[PDB]
Amino acid sequence: KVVARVAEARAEDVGKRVVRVDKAERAKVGVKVGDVVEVKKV
Amino acid sequence: KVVARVAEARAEDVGKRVVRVDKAERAKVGVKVGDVVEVKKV
Image 1 (cartoon, rainbow over the protein chains, first blue to last red):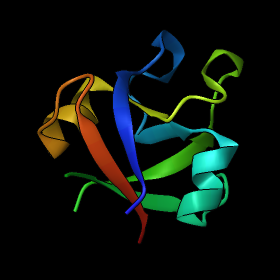
Image 2: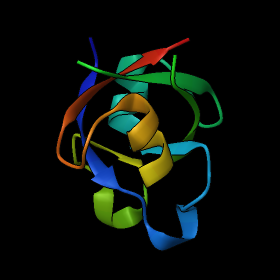
Image 3: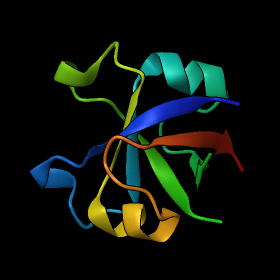
Image 4: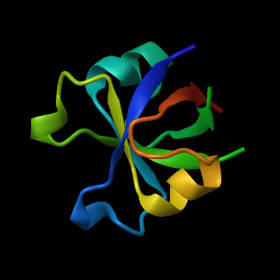
């Protein structure tokens, strides 16, 4: 399971159906920028 | 399933084990800021 702490969106991202993930967690999930991921409560 | 497109972290968030999610997707997942979520590939 790749897990992370949720933080608020920056102003310029409000309204987007988007999650910001740095390179390290993208590598752990095995996705690239622009891929679709699921975000679920643990 | 709550799903979203992955975008790169902003500079100031690099190195954090953190995902940025706006209010709308937090409400759909049913989490608040600071909660832990799972991010998985669909």
